[PDB]
Image (cartoon, rainbow over the protein chains, first blue to last red):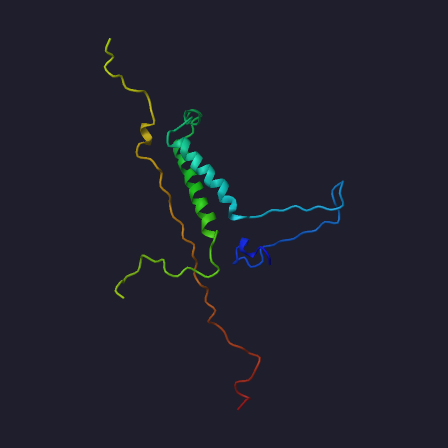
Length: 111
Length: 48
């Protein structure tokens, strides 16, 4: 209710809970979290820019290629990294309402 | 002693056109059809 702007609205209650009768040894209670925050892009946009740094000069690649790795694996992994950031970005800030105007295959433009 | 302006060996020459660019994603979904509907909890004949 308070932090609503930090939740994805089309998953209308984002929460799973579980509760165990047995604490760990020490203090009387505890809790453990996991978020699928779309914030995750802040890590992966850093690696991809840093990757591209190294690879736009082909820095230390001779090691990898010398174990017989092909350079089009680095190209697909980088592509799959860019496409994964695009999926983080497809569901980040996505409206509960659908997008309307976005077509380009249509047969007519006149009115 | 003139060396004839000797060139480097061997550089990032395979990267000279490289950026690289990004692909696209657009998801986006189709509506299901819910037009097969009628209620049963009333009367359509015995009302007459």
